[PDB]
Image: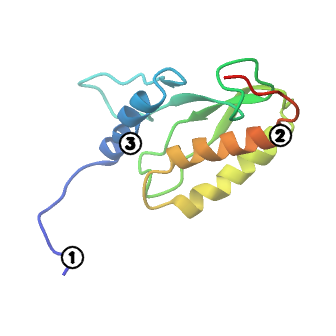
Amino acid sequence: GSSGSSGMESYSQRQDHELQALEAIYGSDFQDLRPDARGRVREPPEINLVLYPQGLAGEEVYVQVELRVKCPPTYPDVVPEIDLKNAKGLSNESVNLLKSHLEELAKKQCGEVMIFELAHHVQSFLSEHNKSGPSSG
C-alpha cells in the first residue's frame, strides 16, 4: 500500500503549521521573530517562547527562561537548535543541563513536530528546579 497522490508540501509549511498553533495555545508567551515577508527568500522561523515552573502561573515565579529556536531548513527531518536566554534563578547554571537534555530529546522526537513537547519538558524542568512557593490561583 502506502501509495497515493503527490502530497507536496514543504518544510516551511510544516514549520509555520506549528507556529499558527502556538499563536492559539500561548498567544503572547509566543512571539515569532521572523524577517520573512510574502515574496522573499525562505529564512529560519525564529521564535521566542517564555516558559515557567507550573503551579505559580503568570505571577511571582522563581526560575524561568525564554526558549529561542530557529529550525534548520529541513526540520522536522532533522532536529532543531535550542537556546535558552534571559534566564532567571538559573545563572546559566542548570540552563546548560536543560539545553543538553533538550538537545537529546529532539533526536527522539525527530520525524514530526517537537516544539510543543520541548516547551512541556522545560516547564517540567523549571518546576523541578523551583523550590518553595505557595499556591494561590
Tag 1: amino acid: Ser
Q: Which of marks 1 and 2 precedes in the sequence? A: 1
- Give the CA distance from mark 2 to mark 1: 46 Å
**Pointer 3 residue:** 15
- Which is closer to the viewer, label 2 or label 1? 2
> x and y percent of residue 1 in the render?
18, 81
Which structural element holds mark 1?
loop
Task: Say if 67 sits above or below 99 in the image.
Answer: above
**Pointer 1 residue:** 2
**In this rendering, position of residue 105 left or right of residue 101:** left
Residue 55's image quarter? top right
Q: Which of marks 3 and 2 precedes in the sequence? A: 3
> x and y percent of residue 86 in the render?
73, 23
Residue at 66 percent of width and 50 percent of height: 102
- Which is closer to the viewer, label 2 or label 3? 2
> x and y percent of residue 72 in the render?
48, 45
Q: Within 10 angstroms of label 2, few (less than 14), some, or many (20 or more) residues?
A: some
Residue at 71 percent of width and 30 percent of height: 65
**In this rendering, position of residue 126 left or right of residue 35:** right
Tag 3: amino acid: Gln
**In this rendering, position of residue 19 left or right of residue 80:** left
Residue 129 is marked as 2
